[PDB]
Amino acid sequence: HNQVSQFKRAVVLNKEKYNPEFKKITYDSPVYFNINEVFNYIYNLNEEVINKIEGEPSL
Amino acid sequence: PKLSNGELVENRQIYFNEKLEFTSSNTSKATKASNGPFNGEFNRFLSRFETKLTDKRL
Image 1 (cartoon, chains in turn yellow, purple):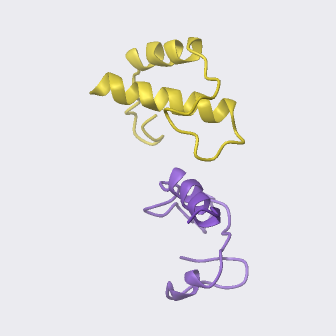
Image 2: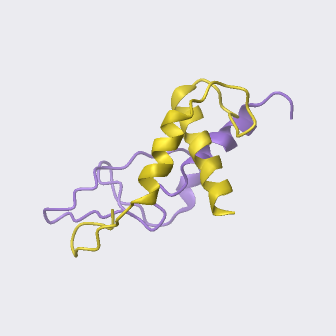
């Protein structure tokens, strides 16, 4: 379930930031999204470390 | 919630009348400002909802 969800999120984000004109741009939309950015997106999600230092927000 | 340009806002009824643009987040000085509970959480909702309202099919 988590991989399916994250795949949908990555495809949607890449689709929108690459095809800004389309409004109802969804997961099944036949618009050019590339897979190298998706693979790197999944790679960076695998090693995410959130900063818990007081003061600055948790990023 | 204070608009800080014309005057502060007492109730929330006037939000329905028109859209409002507020001041900066400050995060300093006496005017601490500080973001609201729902500040920016509704990101895609506005886009798709205005897409629905502007659609000619419905």
